[PDB]
Image (tube, rainbow, N blue to C red):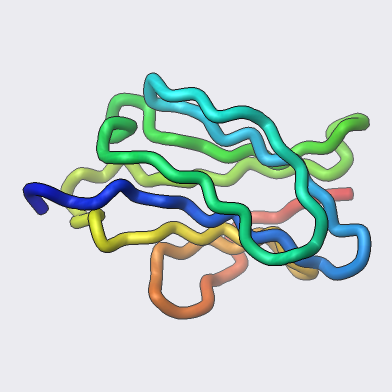
Length: 115
């Protein structure tokens, strides 16, 4: 990993009708915002290898209300030991839980939203 790729993190969201969660994903000397979405598919937030071990990026799921629809997902792992570039982190806020895997195949439930 020398040239590498801007790593884009997928915040997936899908319980079904009226799934809405507002993910605040910012860290690592870089700002994005705090957006909600409807149950559609993917919501992709993108960064480059600047938000490394410095403070990486974390997406926190909340809603315009009390904490209610809440959870706390790590968009990126601050491990420079493992190669990124061709890597993608998918956390999905789905019917069951919040998923957490940087894979090529479907991820695993490792976080959980609320409501």
